[PDB]
Length: 87
Length: 87
View (cartoon, rainbow over the protein chains, first blue to last red):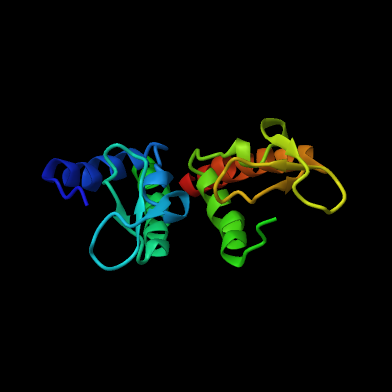
């Protein structure tokens, strides 16, 4: 719900980039590690990340999909691309 | 003692997978880093992990074996398999 252009760019480029180097902020992405709260009037369920620049609260509709995307991204980036560069 | 199917799957696949990328939650596996407590009526000794999805409390019967398995897993996965893929 931050929806701020610098914040959006941060979460879109900087954080995924840092994940390539072992900086994985599970608390800011996984709903199982956050506190459920009714932050937003919009329908649905929401959770409150503790991170400063992680958004005030994030939707938890399909969070297993976010975790799956994190798994695939870690695989590809950390292992496949880096080893391909080494080769 | 969570013994919940999503939680079991999490601890069986997601956490070991993330350990490949430097996310090693020693506090949730090593009993030396946890607080001893009599959570469960079942006989034995138990400790209380601080993790949210680490189980309410874990047995500490042979925890040196858990640490040894962690050592072997780190070795194999992080070093041997990744370097084999590079080769």
